[PDB]
Length: 66
Image (cartoon, rainbow, N blue to C red; front, side):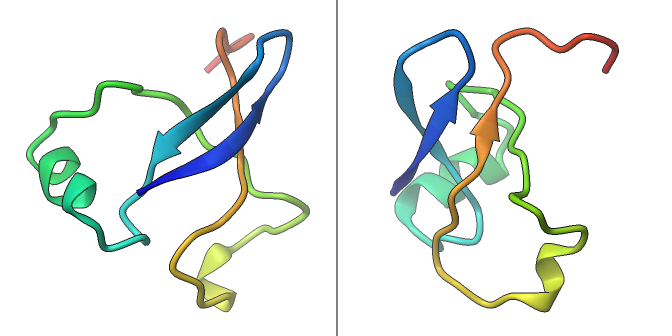
């Protein structure tokens, strides 16, 4: 299950996460990510403090530094 992420400059796309625990997670676990995008944490320093199957994050089409 992919999560709906707001892309800056680009339309809205879905990204596959591990927290979801879906079939996609198994594939990604073997280094088979098709989206290969970075996820941002909304006003959150450590997601470990939260507990949810899915989460909303921001994806960057092109990073500035890394």
